[PDB]
Image (cartoon, rainbow, N blue to C red; front, side, top):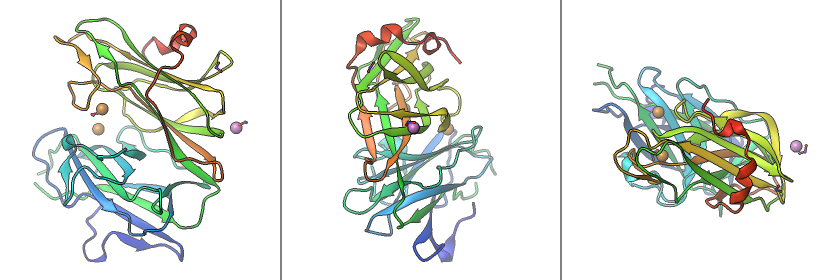
Length: 308
Ligand SMILES: O=N[O-]
Ligand SMILES: O=N[O-]
Ligand SMILES: O=N[O-]
Ligand SMILES: [Cu+2]
Ligand SMILES: [Cu+2]
Ligand code: NI
């Protein structure tokens, strides 16, 4: 957790492997619930694989950490408030660290592909400070990332499901945000999932639908720590399957309508489905921002409507 100083952020591990430490540049937050961000350009231009993550966080002050891969970080320089954004392009989430929900490891043989022609060129670290009650001292919290240039037999990726058009009228008891897309790639295997909502979300659920049958991928209270939780049973999604997600929102407590957006007063319905694929079939990211089968949600399991 200590700042690195003279030895810097790159530690050789083996002939082909190295650790990259992505830390805050000795920051001292002034308010509670501060969101700090920073970027590291990858040290290698060629293709590499992220096979492990080690959290390096002060247990007193850090609420959560997020690590992203992208090509255009929102800001240049040393560090910034993530109120100005994380990445200008698509931020590909790699890792979440929650205080009250310790992370689960990548399965062995699984890595994210980064760098090269098409991979992420930058890491962006987001650190959410909770208490900030310490003393006035400098903080260097972050993540140690294990990189290798040995190709991995299985490639990790992210299937992101997000609402874009949700409107939650003020005081409205239940507002559903439904998301659905047909899967049209090679088989992916879901091993982890993360849900994200702001203060109005009560339950988020995602399913694979295969010939009318709903198989649960993940279902979580978004007010609980937003870590990646492992899937109960590894769920394969194959060509012709439908991915379906529902967030349940309340409008109660709000004087005005709440829509999708980036601030605390806005909402989000995000479901991050972390998968692996065979390397020769793999693609690193997919997104569903649509609702292609809206009448299919008539047979959605009851669990998706009651809170956990
Ligand atoms: O039931 N969707 O294949
Ligand atoms: O992915 N079929 O077990
Ligand atoms: O979750 N704030 O965009
Ligand atoms: Cu947090
Ligand atoms: Cu959000
Ligand atoms: Ni399988």
